[PDB]
Amino acid sequence: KSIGLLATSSEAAYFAEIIEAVEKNCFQKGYTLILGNAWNNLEKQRAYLSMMAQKRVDGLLVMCSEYPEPLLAMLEEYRHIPMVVMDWGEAKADFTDAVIDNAFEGGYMAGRYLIERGHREIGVIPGPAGRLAGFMKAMEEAMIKVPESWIVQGDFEPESGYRAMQQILSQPHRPTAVFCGGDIMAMGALCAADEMGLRVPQDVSLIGYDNVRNARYFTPALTTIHQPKDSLGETAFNMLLDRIVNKREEPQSIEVHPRLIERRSVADGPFRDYRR
Amino acid sequence: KSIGLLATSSEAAYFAEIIEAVEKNCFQKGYTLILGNAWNNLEKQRAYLSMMAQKRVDGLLVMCSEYPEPLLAMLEEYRHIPMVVMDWGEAKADFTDAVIDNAFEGGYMAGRYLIERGHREIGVIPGPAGRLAGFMKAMEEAMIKVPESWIVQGDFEPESGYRAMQQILSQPHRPTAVFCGGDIMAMGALCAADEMGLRVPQDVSLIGYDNVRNARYFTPALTTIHQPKDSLGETAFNMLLDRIVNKREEPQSIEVHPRLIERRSVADGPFRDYRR
Ligand SMILES: [Mg+2]
Ligand SMILES: [Mg+2]
Image (cartoon, each protein chain N blue to C red):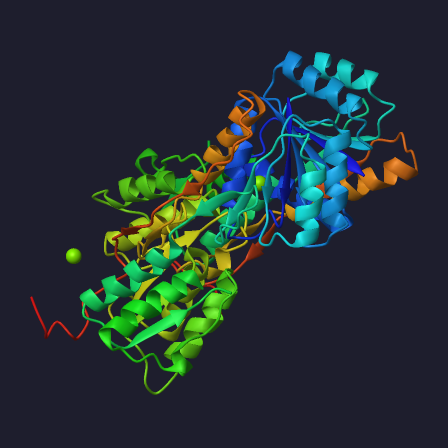
């Protein structure tokens, strides 16, 4: 009773929560976990692949940022060992299980809550895209220009959000609201504002994305887009099961929908002049 | 290379930060990790053991909170497999490696710092230790008495720190500083002080324990005790890599020392008056 788990990075703030879910379920079902953590290397990922085969694991489970031809090749050579390939976005007619998170709808929702709160001068601390694409469509649809000097890439880690917010806030003209593409990154943004002497949400409104466990325990309690992370691994982990037992060779798609969690990091903006 | 890890719980406060350092070191070398959480069932651990032997892991890391004779005996059968069996707890004359975290010392440094900064009416949010004990000695030694109404425990998680902080802060009379035995928990206390209109540390000073990865980016930047978890993880790993090749049958002692990290959550107390 063991299961392989070939990841792209346990420590990749994005994925991470998913793993914990795959994990806690295994222990919960007293299985053994055989953790492989690649990082995009045909051989390393290969290595990890054969080893789980030799340790005769009762199920596989892949989580990959990409799925290039080579990887895809290997993956087939090991079809005898039952699995679940979590493939985000691009539903390519292969044999991978499609994960549809509705990030595009996620970012949409965020950018829209801000327009509705009356903000028109907006900042964005983008991660390393669908979300973002979502946010620009509402900005576009509302005719809000976004100065390029108010768009600063983060990396999912607090120091990046800390450096990003300070860059944005530290300009003659600044926005009244900032869209943060990651709750963790948003924790580093709340800090910088505070250290600069800015009252959040009073001087700057902030909305993040994820709804990480601690997000409600931020100061202030963080308004964000709840992205079901630890629902995905439990499902993926169940698709693995049925697959090994019931012999479910026919694939499945895991799709979720985003939801806005209203809390306390967002205030009314100056454009409450237009409507009530 | 495959490495096996037997632990009571991967998700337990103390271990959590230790297991991730291990994991991080594994993937760095390219090793695979075989994870198992046994929880205290002689039988279940006795099952993970046989299987790991069966999967031919190159080495074993054992960390268990308690090692009853019977666990120790079964481990003795598997001594052909290189292992590091971490033992917190009173050093015994057996093959276990000793782990010495100097918690009582961290607790004391914490108390003392508070007392030095001028506070005398202190509150406490203990975890479900020896740190608490070392904390109380710095108290007892400065004649300070800490009332029961100002002691409320948590369980490592944020809501627990929130609820206890609210409880202590809602007292007709309140401490001027609080000792939180765990940063995560402190994350919650910090949010609680805020939602009650109290400013940290203008109105209340706060000190945590651990110095978790994000602490510096808490709001405000947290004053806490750095308790080394990553170093321990690193240390055990390397000891295991050593035994794998330099097959060493000599128990080792791992000692770490806590260190105070002065950030921005603690201010001068009323009784502060010894210098600048
Ligand atoms: Mg983990
Ligand atoms: Mg509506």
